[PDB]
Image (cartoon, rainbow, N blue to C red):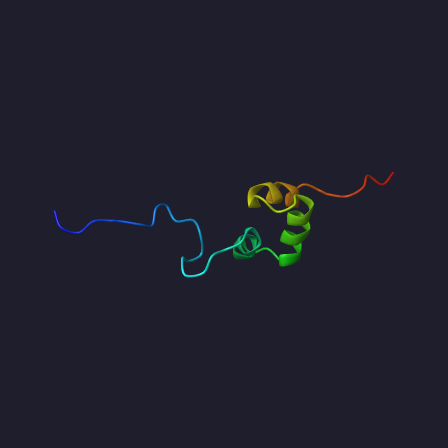
Length: 64
């Protein structure tokens, strides 16, 4: 016996001391706040996964 393992489950963030952000996350991935911003904004800012899809996905008004 002895010892255990409480708290900290899975852990999904660049540290526990400071909380992350859907944006800060993208920043960690290597994306510019802008990119994440534009995306976030577009997709409001709920999930970072959705934004990504948007990011990659060509966004713009079909010109011609």
